[PDB]
Image: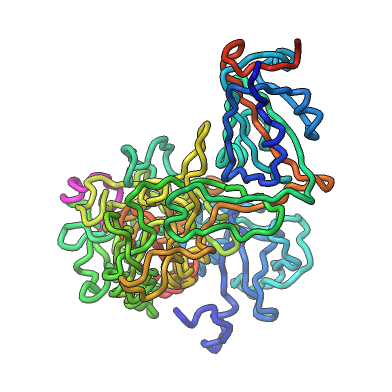
Amino acid sequence: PDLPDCDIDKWLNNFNVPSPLNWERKIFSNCNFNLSTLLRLVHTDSFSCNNFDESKIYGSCFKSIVLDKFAIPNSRRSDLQLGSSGFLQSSNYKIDTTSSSCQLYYSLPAINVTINNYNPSSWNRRYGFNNFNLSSHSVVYSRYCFSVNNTFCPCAKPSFASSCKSHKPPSASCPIGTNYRSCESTTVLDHTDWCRCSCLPDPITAYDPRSCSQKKSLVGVGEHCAGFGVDEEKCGVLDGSYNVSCLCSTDAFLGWSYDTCVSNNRCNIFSNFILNGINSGTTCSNDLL
Amino acid sequence: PSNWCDGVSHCPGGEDENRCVRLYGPNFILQVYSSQRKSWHPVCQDDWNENYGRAACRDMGYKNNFYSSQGIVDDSGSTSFMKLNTSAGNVDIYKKLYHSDACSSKAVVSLRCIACGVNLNSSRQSRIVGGESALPGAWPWQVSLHVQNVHVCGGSIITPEWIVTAAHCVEKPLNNPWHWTAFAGILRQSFMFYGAGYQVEKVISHPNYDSKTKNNDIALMKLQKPLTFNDLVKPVCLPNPGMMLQPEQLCWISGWGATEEKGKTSEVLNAAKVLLIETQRCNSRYVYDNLITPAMICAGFLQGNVDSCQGDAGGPLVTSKNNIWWLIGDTSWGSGCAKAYRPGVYGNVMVFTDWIYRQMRADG
C-alpha cells in the first residue's frame, strides 16, 4: 500500500558475488516481495525450508528477512547438509538450524558474474595480507580459523635473535602496545646458541597448542573466520633490525584453498533465507489478493 | 671381541666365522652364518637333539643357560636351511651343518636360551610424569646402580651376571668397578641400604663411544655373583634383527627419574607408557638438527608431559609383542623433562646386540 518493492531479485543476480570467507548479508524490511516472481526471474535449482511451510510463505507478513549469499565450490557441495562438519560449515558459515530458515540454490551465467574475495579478519590484514591473487571465477574458502587477541605478534625480538647462531628466526618490530613473540634458547650437543620458538611448524601441525599463541576456533551463527595460519617463521626478513616492520609474506598465510563454482557454464551461488516475525510487521507479501 | 663376525678369519682354525650364531624374529628362529654365501640361514628341526642346543647357547654368549627349544613353521621366507647330519663322529655342531633345500619336518627351530620377557600381571602403572602409582613385579629386570650408596643411573638385566646401562654414567673418573653397587628387585629407594647390594666386578664401555655427540652410548656392568631368579627378578630377552617395529608402537619406559626437570629423584620406581618416534622424523633440521646417529632412538611424545628425566638414564625401553618383552632402547640423555618439542632420546640397543654377545663370550 503506497510502498515500494523489496527488489530481492535484483540483489541475488548481482554480478558481484562474494566468497564463503567474506559472505555478504543484507537486511530487507518494510517492503513488498514476491517469491513467485523471484522463482521465475532467477534460475533456482532447489528450494527447501527447515522447520517451516513453503505454502505459508506466500502472502505472509514478516518483521525482517535476513539473506546471505556466496558462490559455492564444486568440491564442498556435500558440506551444505544440515548437521555437517565440513570446511564450509566449520570454518566459513554455520546455518541457523533452530530458526525457521529456507535454503536457496540459485545460479548465474559465468559470462557476466565477477567473483569477489575478501579477508574479514582484522589481524590477518594487519600483519601483511593485502588481497587474494586468484584466477577468474575462483571461490576462496577457509580450511580452519585461528583466533588471536590484540597483543599477538608473529615476529620475535631482534635483540633476542642477535645471539641465535642456529635457527635464528626472522625478526622485526611490533606495533607499540603489543606483546612480543614467545621464544626461548637452550643448548644441546655443541649447539651453544640453540633457539626454538612456539608454533614452529604450521599452526595446524603445531603439536603443543597451549604454548602456541594461535588458538583454533569454530565459527558460530553470524560470525566469520577468525584468521589464517600465517606461518611465523616466514614473517619478516633475516637479520632484521627495528627499522623493518613485522610483515608476513603471501606464502606465509595457510589454512585456505580454492575451487571454481561453474556448473554447465553457470556459476552456482548458495543463498540462505531467515524469516523473523511470522504474521507480524509491515513488509507483507502480495502473492494473494 | 671385535674380531668376531666380521667376515675375515683371524684364528687359524676359523672359529670366528664358522661359529657366528644369532637368533631371529619374535618367535626366536635360529640362524647360522654361512661362510660360503655370506648370508644367514635358519636351521632344520630334523635329526636335532638338545645337546646341540647346549652348544648353540654356549656360543651365543649365554653359557649353559637353556630354557626350551621346539620346532616352528618357517616364516622368514628363506630359500635355504641348514641341515644336520648324525653320520659325523665329531662333537661340533657347525661342522655337522650343511645346506639343504628344505627340511623333512617342514619346521625350523625356535631356540630359547633363557626364560625372559615375562612378568606378573599389572593393571595400572603410569608412574612417570602425569600418572598414578605402580605395583611390584611388573618390571623385574629394572635395577638401580649406586655410587657411594646414592642413585646415579638405572639399569636393566639380560642374564644373571650382566647389567646394561649408559656409558655416560660410567665415564671417567667413574670407570672403576669398585665404586659401583647395584641393587635388584627393590621398589623403594629407602630399602636398598642394608645388604641388598650386588657389586660390579668389571665395567665395560663401548670402544667407539664419543662424549661430544654422546653417540654409541652403551655400558655393561658384570656382577661377581649371578642373580638368583624368582618372581621379583627376571631378565628381558635381547631383541633380534628382523622385527617390523611399526611407528607409534606402544612402548614402556621405567626408572627412578625425577617428576620434573632439575628436580630430585623419585623415592619409588616410576614407569609409564610412551610412543616410538621415527628416526628420519627426529634427525631433521627441526627436531634435533641431524643430531640423531643411526645408533640412536627417539621415543616419547612430541607434545611432551610423558618423558624421561635425570635419573631415568640406564632405564629400559620395552615393548610387548607375543607376550615377550624386548629391550630395544637405553636412556642416554634427555633435553628437559616432560616438555614439548624436546622428547626423550634413547640409545639403540639393536645396533649393539652383536657387541653385547662379543663381550659376553670373551668374559664367560
- Colouring method of the image: rainbow
Could you tell me which quadrant the N terminus of chain B lies in?
bottom left
Which residue is more in the foreground, B27 or A78? Answer: A78
Q: In the figure, residue A175 lies in which quadrant?
A: bottom left
Q: Is residue A24 left or right of residue B282?
A: right
| Residue ID at (57%, 22%) | A64
Could you tell me which quadrant the C terminus of chain B lies in?
bottom left
Percent coordinates x, y for residue B323 in the rendering: 53, 45
Q: Main secondary structure of the magenta part?
A: loop
| Residue ID at (65%, 80%) | B35
Examine the rendered structure and indicate whether residue B179 appears above or below residue B192: below
Examine the rendered structure and indicate whether residue B356 appears above or below residue B160: below
Percent coordinates x, y for residue A104 in the rendering: 71, 30
| Residue ID at (37%, 54%) | B340
Q: Is residue B17 left or right of residue B108?
A: left
Q: Is residue B179 left or right of residue A13?
A: left
Magenta residues, as a range?
Answer: B182-194
Examine the rendered structure and indicate whether residue A182 appears above or below residue A241: above
Which residue is more in the foreground, A276 or B33? Answer: A276
Q: Is residue A108 visible?
A: yes
